[PDB]
Amino acid sequence: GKVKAGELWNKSKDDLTKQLAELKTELGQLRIQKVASSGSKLNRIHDIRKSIARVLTVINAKQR
Amino acid sequence: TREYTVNLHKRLHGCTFKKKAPNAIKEIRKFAQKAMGTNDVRIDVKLNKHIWSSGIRSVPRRVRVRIARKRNDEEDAKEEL
Amino acid sequence: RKITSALRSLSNATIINEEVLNAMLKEVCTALLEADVNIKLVKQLRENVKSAIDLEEMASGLNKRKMIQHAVFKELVKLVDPGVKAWTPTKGNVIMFVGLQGSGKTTTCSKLAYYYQRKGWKTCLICADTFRAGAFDQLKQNATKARIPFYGSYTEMDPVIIASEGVEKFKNENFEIIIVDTSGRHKQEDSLFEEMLQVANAIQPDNIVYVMDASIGQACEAQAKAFKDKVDVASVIVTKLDGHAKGGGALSAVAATKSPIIFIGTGEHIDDFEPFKTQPFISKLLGMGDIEGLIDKVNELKLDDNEALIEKLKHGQFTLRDMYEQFQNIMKMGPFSQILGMIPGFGTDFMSKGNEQESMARLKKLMTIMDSMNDQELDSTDGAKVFSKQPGRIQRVARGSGVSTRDVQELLTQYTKFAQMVKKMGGIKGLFKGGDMSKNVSQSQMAKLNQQMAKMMDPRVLHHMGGMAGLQSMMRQFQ
Amino acid sequence: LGFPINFLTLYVTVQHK
Amino acid sequence: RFICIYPAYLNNKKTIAEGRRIPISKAVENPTATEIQDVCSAVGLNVFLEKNKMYSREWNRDVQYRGRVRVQLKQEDGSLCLVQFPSRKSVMLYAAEMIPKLKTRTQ
Amino acid sequence: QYQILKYPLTTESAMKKIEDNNTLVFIVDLKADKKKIKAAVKKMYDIQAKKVNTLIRPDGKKKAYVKLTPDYDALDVANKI
RNA sequence: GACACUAAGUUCGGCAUCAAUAUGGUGACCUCCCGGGAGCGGGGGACCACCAGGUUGCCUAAGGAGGGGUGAACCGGCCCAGGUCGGAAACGGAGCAGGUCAAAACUCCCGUGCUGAUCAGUAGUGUC
RNA sequence: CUGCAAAGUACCCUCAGAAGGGAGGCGAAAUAGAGCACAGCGAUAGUCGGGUGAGAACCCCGACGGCCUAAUGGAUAAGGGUUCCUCAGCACUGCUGAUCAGCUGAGGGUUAGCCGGUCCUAAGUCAUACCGCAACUCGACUAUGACGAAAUGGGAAACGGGUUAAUAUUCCCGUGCCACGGGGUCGAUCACGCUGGGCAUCGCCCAGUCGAACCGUCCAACUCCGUGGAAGCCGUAAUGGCAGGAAGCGGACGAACGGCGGCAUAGGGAAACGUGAUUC
C-alpha cells in the first residue's frame, strides 16, 4: 500500500537493501509489543510482510 | 434438651444383618424427628461411631442420646451420652 | 495541548525516526514559544535534549522511540520542575508566602492550613497584606471556611508589634504552624522588598515559599532570583496547574534557586493542594496524564477508608444502595478524570470526551432523586423491580425531586445496567457482600489483615489496590 | 471493576441528553 | 403588566387550595392554557400564551397541565380595553363559560 | 523467506527462567534448529548465547529456551522490548 | 368441734364501656369580596371531623373529655434539606426523603360493669 | 427459501442465569426469530457434624468406621494423544444426583554435552548391479551399500539441594564428570540410645533417627610367580588336588549398584539428625 512497486523499482539496489532492513526493523518492533501488548493496527504488520516480499522480488528481477 | 433411649434399633433386625448399621442410623433420625416434633436431625458423629462400633452387622439394641431443640423452626442436635 | 497529540502522533510505525524526532522536537518546540522568542531558555532544553542522545541509548530490551520520551518528559520536568518531597516540620513552624501580585498567595495559605490541619497540626493564618484593604477580609473568610484561625496583623507600625501579637495568639491557642500571607509585590520594588526583608528578620521564619503562577513567562528567572537574594526563600508552590499553561517557569525558578517545589496548586477549591511534582507534568506532558491521574485515583482514595471520616456517607454505609455508593464513586469519580473512561460505548456521545465538573453535577442530581426514595426501595435486592410492581412510587419520587417521570425511569435503567458490571459477575450481590461485609472493610478487612507494619505510603498503595473492585478479577485472571 | 463500572456510568450520562 | 391566568384557576377538578378561583358550578373539566388563550383572543382581548410557565401549586409536570396566559385589561392611559372585562374574575368566568363550546371539545 | 525469531514468549515460567536462570524464551519457526536460533538471537540483541533447548509445541510453532552468558544477563535484554 | 349463709380477701382469665351541648383550638371543604404583574397580601359568611379542659341530659348494670403505641412509599396534621415551581431579586408556593404530634384513622394498657375459675380460709350469723 | 430493509427484538416481570418463559416491540408476514414462503464378583462401606451452593446421600473439611499389601501402593514399555494444570460452566456424557469430572468452553503447560533417541551390529530386511521372466510393482544366488534393538542386546560423561498451578538427573544453586558356595546393599526383623506421637489399671504401641551421582581408596574368588618338599597329606555343600610337586609362607594380576574417606558448616528435617547385629 504505502509502498508501491514503481517506487521500489525507482529505488537503487542499495536503497532497496536499506529499505529492506528498515521494514524488517518495523516488523521486529511490531512483533515485540507483539508478545507484550499489541498497540495496534493489524493491517500493517501484514503489509510489512508483503512490502518485504515485493522488495525481495524486485531485487531478484533487477539482479540486485 | 433431654435424654432419650432409642430403641427403634430393634426394628433394624427386620433388615438383613450385613446392613444393620445404616438402618440404625436412620431409625435414630426418625425417632428424634418424631417425639420431638420440633427436632431436625443432625446426628453428631459420636452417635454414628457408637452404632458402627462393632461393625456394620452388630448394632446395639439401644442407644442413649442427648438431644436439644431450638424452638423456633424445629431443629435438633444430638449426640451420645 | 495539540502537541500532546504529537505524542501518539508520534507513536505509530517504527519504519522512520530521527527525522520523526527533530520534527516533533521543532513541532513541540514550535507550539510552545520556542528559543530565543520570549527568552532564550529553550535553546538550552532543545540542547540538553540533544546532548543526551549522543551520550546514551535506551537500555536494550526496549524500543528507542519510547525511551526518547522518558528523556523528553524527563527534560520537560526539568524545564518547569521535577519533584518528589514535602517540608519537614518541627515543634514550632512559621512560614511566609511571598511573590508577585496575583500569584495565589492568600489562597495557598488557606490551602496549606487545611492540608496541615488534617495532619493534626495547630495552624494560625496571619493576614499581613495591608496595602490591599479587602485583603484581610479575604483571608478571614477563607480561615472560616477551613476553620483555621486568622490574625489580621494590622499593626504595621513596627513588625515588632506583629511579632508580639502572633506570639501571644500562638501561645494562648496552642498554634504550631504559623502561615504569614504577605502582600504581592514586584521583585524590583525596593521599599516593599525591604519591608519583606525586615519582616523576615523580626519574625524568624523557617520556610519562605515563593508562590509562582504556572503561567508566568520569561521573567520567572529574574523574579525567583530577586526574591531569593533578598529574602531568603526556600521552597516554591506552583499554582494554577489546573490550567493549560506548560509550566516552564518552574524549571526557571528551580534552576536559579536550587530549592525544591513543595506543592502544586490545582483548582480553586480549599482542598486543591497536592505534591505530585514534575511527574504529573511529565505525564502532562503525555497522554498518560490520565495514567498519572490514577495517582488521584489512589492518592485521594485512602481518603476513603479511615475512621469513617467520609461522614458515613461517601462509599461506606451509603454503600448499601450498591447503588448509592457506586454513584458516589462515579460523585467522586467525576470528580476529575484519571483516565480515559474505557467506557464500553460510543453513541453520539457527541464528544463526550470530558466535562468534570459537569460529570459530578450529574451524579449529584441522581442522588437527589434517590433522596426521594424510601428505605424499602433503597435497600431492596432489586430496586428497579419495586417500581415495576408499584409504578405509583415512580410518580412520588419524581414529584419530590423536581424531576420528570422519565428521569426516574432513566435512573432506574442506569441502576439496572450498573448492578448487572457490578453484576460483570456476580453483580449485586457478591459485590455488596464482600461489599456489605467488605468494600472498604472489605479492603479494610484486608486493610486490617494486610496493612499492619506497612508505613503510610505502603497503606495508600494497598488502598489503591483495593480500588480494584476487579482486583479480585485481576488476581483470579492471573491464576 | 473500576474501569467498566466507571466507564459505563460515564458512557451512560453522555448518551442520555 | 398584563394579568395572569393559570389553568388551575378554571379547573373544576381542583380544590380551593389546589388553585381554583371560580365556583365549581362555573369551573371546567380540564382547561388548557391554549384553550384559554384561544377564547380570549377571540373576543377582542389582547393576550399572549406563556407555553412553558408552570403554576406553583401544580404537582403534575405533563403538558395538558402546564402553561400560562396573559391578558391586557387596562391600557397605558388607564381605560379598560373592553368595558365588559373589569376584573380578572371577569375573564376567568368568561373563559370558563366559552371553553365547553370550543369545537375541539364538542367533537 | 522466513525469519528465525518470531517473538518473545512471555509467561510466568519464562519470567522465572529469565530472573533466576537468566534465560530468554522465544517462539521461532519450527525448523530453525538450534544453531540457527543461537545465531539469530545473538545478532538481534547483541549477546552471547550459551545454549539453546527447543520444543515443538503444540501451538504449531516451536519454543526455544536460550540461556545467555552471565555478563550478558537477561532481565535487561528483555526489558528493552 | 364439724358443717352452712351474708359481707369479703388472693390470683390468672372472659365479656363489655352512651348521648346531646357552650367556649376556645387544629384540620378539611365550600362560598363571597378588596388588593396585586406572578408566587400571593387582606377580609366575610357555611358545612364536617377531631382535640382541650367545662356542663347536662333524667341517660345505662356500667360509660371517666385517663395513659401509651403506630402513623402507613404516597394515600393524617405539623416542620420541611435537597431538588422543583413563580420571581431580575427579595422572597413565596406545591412538596418527597428526614424529623415530629393536645387534635385523620387504627390500635393497646388504665380505670369502671357483669363474669367463669382459683386460693384463702380471717368477719359476723345459723345449724348439729 | 430470514427479510424489501437488520428493522436480527428496547423496556418490565420471572429465574441460579447474557439460559428459557411471560409481556412487549419490528415487519405485509415471526407457525419469516437465526441449518430461520442399575444386587450376585473374598473389595458387602459408610455414619455424624460442618463448608459451598438456587439446589447436596454420593463436591469439599473434620471425626468416627472400614477396604487394598506383587496390590486399589511406587516407577515404567507399548498403545492413547492433551485425557495433564487453571478458570468458567452443566445442554451432552457419567448405570441415580451433582455445585464434581476423564464431560463442555477458553487459556496455560513438556526447557538436557553427561536420561533416552541418535552410533554399533542380531535374526533378518531393503536398494542398486547382475541374471531370469512375454513382462513387471515379480523371482533365488552373488557382489556393493544401506536398514534392523527407546522397558529388555552393545554403549564416552551427573550428583545433591531448591523451585511451579502444571516440567525437571533438562530450570535455579552448588559441585562433579566426558568428548572433541562365597562376597554383599536395600528391605525386614532383633538389641540399646536419642527425637515426637498414641494410650492410660498395666507399660506398652507407632513413626523418625536421613544424606546421591561422582572422585579416591580397599578386597574376595579365579589365574599365576617364588619359596617350600608332602610317597598320605591338602581341600569342599559336593565334585576334587598333588613329585608333571600338596599344605604352609611370601608375592603379581585382580570385584560389587559393596566398604571406607571426600563430595556436605551441599541438601533435607519439627526434632533427634544413632550404634551393633541377623537373615540378606
Image: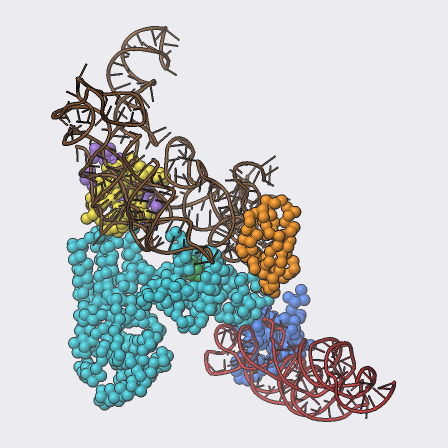
Chain colours: A purple, B orange, C cyan, D green, E blue, F yellow, G red, H brown
Of the 4 image quadrants, the one containing the N terminus of chain A is top left
In this view, the residue in front, H79 or C357, is: H79
Residue at 31% across, 83% down? C174
Q: How many labels does the image show?
A: 0
Residue C183 x, y percent position in the rendering = 26, 81
Q: In screen coordinates, is C272 left or right of C346?
A: left
Q: In the visual, does A29 lie left or right of H207? A: left
Q: Quadrant of residue C86?
A: bottom left
**Quadrant hosting residue G111:** bottom right
* Above or below E77: residue B2: above
Q: Nearer the viewer, residue E6 or A59?
A: A59
In the picture, measured across the screen, residue H39 lies left or right of residue C67, that is right
Residue C411 visible within the image: yes
**For the point 19% across and 78% down, which residue is it?**
C231
Q: Can residue F40 be seen in this view?
A: no
The answer to which of A47 and G21 lies nearer the viewer is G21
Measuring from the top left, give residue C262's x and y in whole percent. Answer: 26, 71
Residue sitting at x 23%, y 66%: C81
Q: In which quarter of the image is the C terminus of chain A?
A: top left
Give percent across and percent down for residue A21: 23, 42
Q: Residue at x 16, y 57 (%)?
A: C51
The percent position of residue B63, horizontal first and vertical second, equals 60, 56
Q: Which quadrant of the view contains residue C24?
A: bottom left
